[PDB]
Length: 48
Length: 199
Image (cartoon, rainbow over all chains, first blue to last red; front, side, top):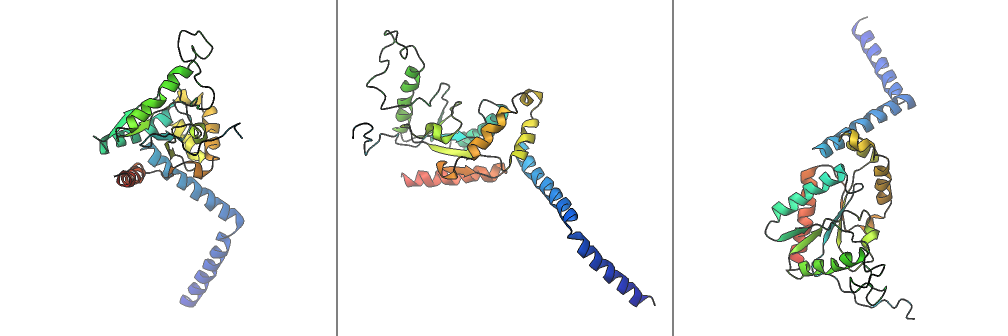
């Protein structure tokens, strides 16, 4: 009633999060974040 | 077939002059600093074997098959005699004189901003490309100077992508990275290889 149920809940939630993270909206947001972070390193080097 | 009649041989300076182009229009803050740092690196690391000369006047009017002697004397009062062609033509063999001493020389030309502008001339120089990876970085880098450069930001951008659209094969070397020290070594090893090549 506790350990098996918690394991099932954690597994289902992890699968749901993994499926949801690869949607087009989340992927686009992550790509925007990655591009913004990549610009910053080049900017810091050029300012140095 | 004497309309052009290109000779099989051309006269070029013994040591290749080094010209820095990019990342934008010269005479502006960003380009001036990004080239002055490298100039400084060349003066210091290769001290005692490299002479730095600045070409304040124009250098893109280096022609050889126009006429026998356009504006030979300053007293002719001709259109080209009183023009700027005389001093530019007289600056050509100064580079030759610097090259015949075996000491490597650079060119601090403030007018040339594209390799094709100085590719058909008799100089045949080494062209160094300092470029920003993306224009998104370059715009904010120009923003980092102050309100003075915002006035000229517009014209400062087409000079970037026009030079970017030039094929990489036109340039001799490419400095496509952001770190100052690693790009600094990128030129140092290339010029050491060149130094060993002609010795």
